[PDB]
Amino acid sequence: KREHWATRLGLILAMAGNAVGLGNFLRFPVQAAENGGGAFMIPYIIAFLLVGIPLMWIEWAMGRYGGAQGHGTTPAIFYLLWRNRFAKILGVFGLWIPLVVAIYYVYIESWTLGFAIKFLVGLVPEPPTDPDSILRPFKEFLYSYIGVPKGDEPILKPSLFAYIVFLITMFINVSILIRGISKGIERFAKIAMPTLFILAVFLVIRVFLLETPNGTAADGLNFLWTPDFEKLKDPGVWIAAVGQIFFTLSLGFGAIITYASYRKDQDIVLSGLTAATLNEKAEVILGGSISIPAAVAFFGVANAVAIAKAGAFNLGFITLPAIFSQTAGGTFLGFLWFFLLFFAGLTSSIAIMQPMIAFLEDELKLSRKHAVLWTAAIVFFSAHLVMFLNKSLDEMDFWAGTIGVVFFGLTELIIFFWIFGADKAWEEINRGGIIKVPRIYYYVMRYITPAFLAVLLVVWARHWTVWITRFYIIGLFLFLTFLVFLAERRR
Ligand SMILES: CCCCCCCCO[C@@H]1O[C@H](CO)[C@@H](O)[C@H](O)[C@H]1O
Ligand SMILES: CC(C)C[C@H](N)C(=O)O
Ligand SMILES: CCCCCCCC
Ligand SMILES: CCCCCCCC
Ligand code: NA
Ligand code: NA
């Protein structure tokens, strides 16, 4: 018998753990600070209402609909809606995207674990005062961990501690996934989400008390929420907003679908809305009130924007620890920060590995033990690419996490609302609950959302170390297409 979420709330809490992750505390501050903070929020809100919320309901519908027929993954669920062979091929992306994203997501999550260990024990840089002299020791601290070469070289030389901690991170993910849906993920989400909420609120309160001659914690909140309608015409802001919305809500990652497949009795309208608002609260209230207000309080708005533009990890791994280190007990604040990130990423990595696990369980009839171990071997083996090859992690985040989920999000929209039938999809979404979707969203999900994506997708169009990554992940797609072929012959 297929696994089962014990309670309706347990699925909602695990869905919040799926959504709330490193994108709320690491990706969102960088995206907002890059695109002007407040000027970024208007397209972010519009993208959340026109793309985020509707796609959250759809994927939950396809998952619950497919889960009633014993299928959790997209290759089988796409075929149920569209009885076509090409539907199974496009469904491979629902296994390929979560696999490629988990290759680098779990590794970045291992950094938060390793940093939390050394910050707890107190093995952090020592500063004695220009901002560069406080920020430089922590920049060298991160570069020694992941093994960045001095200047430019195609090969990374990560530390032995980082490689060992990555093994521990893979072991922790397996330990949770090996126990299953109810006894493992649902059990862990009930504990991690309150811990996530308590740590973040404590950090937000501590950050809010920071004040220097150059800035105030409230100055960063004013920078993030004062809108700028002049930058509304910038297409780059709309691209960053929709891409951010896809990432934080786990849209196009095939993770919402498999999670929803383990519960037939569920109001997907209220459950999908609760999980989204829970994620957006942690994103713009908690994640938005830590990194940006602390950076602005110590360096000002102008320098805080330049810091977020220097790198994706420059804020949460370098600037925020160095800022904390200038305060009493800041080494412990650093520990609480990365411990906050570790629980945020751990509850999301187990969510993006279950799709490949559910495929081996449901389509190839493998036991959960063998399913978890085999997908873990795929993730651990492939992770050596992003561990040692410079810019290899950036190529995976682009193809699978950036352009893939947008392409896959439009694909599941068309299959569900255009091929399967808009009225059948509308019936399936609002079925089985007291909360019903307003009728206006029927036109958003049938006309607005697909046109909004397609228009934004075509308006997007305007070192050999990347070819190894392209060559590798292409083989990952061919390998998963092969198993979908094998699972079709067994049936
Ligand atoms: C399935 C493939 C397994 C490959 C295992 C390779 C492990 C290499 O690990 C190496 O150990 C060094 C020890 O100093 C460290 O510098 C680094 O972690 C790494 O270069
Ligand atoms: C599930 C992951 C791919 C994304 C997750 N929502 C995060 O922001 O970390
Ligand atoms: C330290 C010698 C081997 C390092 C390269 C192996 C990584 C797969
Ligand atoms: C001499 C160490 C280089 C290791 C390269 C690893 C490529 C996967
Ligand atoms: Na998120
Ligand atoms: Na999570």
Image (cartoon, rainbow, N blue to C red):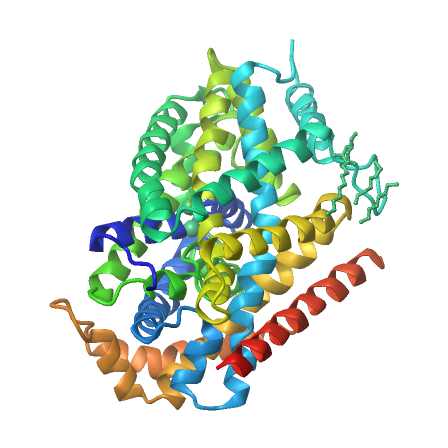
Q: In this view, does 331 lie to the left or right of 8?
A: right
Q: Which of 52 and 483 is in front in this view?
A: 483
Q: Can residue 108 be seen in this view?
A: yes
**Quadrant assignment, res 124:** top right
Q: Residue 394 in the image: x percent, y percent?
A: 68, 53
Q: Which of 152 and 464 is in front in this view?
A: 464
Q: Which residue lies furthest to the top in this view?
A: 128
Q: Residue 60 in the image: x percent, y percent?
A: 33, 67
Give the residue at x 53% y 29%.
320
How many numbered marks appear? 0
144 w.r.t. 460: above or below: above
Q: Nearer the viewer, residue 245 or 1?
A: 1
Give the residue at x 33% y 50%.
14
Q: Residue 110 in the image: x percent, y percent?
A: 58, 37
Q: In this view, does 188 lie to the left or right of 379?
A: left
Give the residue at x 40% y 64%.
258
260 w.r.t. 33: above or below: below
69 w.r.t. 245: above or below: below
Q: Is residue 343 left or right of residue 436?
A: right
Give the residue at x 68% y 35%.
163
Q: Can residue 458 be seen in this view?
A: no
- The quarter of the picture where the N terminus appears is bottom left
Q: Locate ligand 4 by image quadrant.
A: top right
Q: Residue 434 in the image: x percent, y percent?
A: 11, 68
Q: Residue furthest left?
A: 434
**Quadrant assignment, res 321:** top right
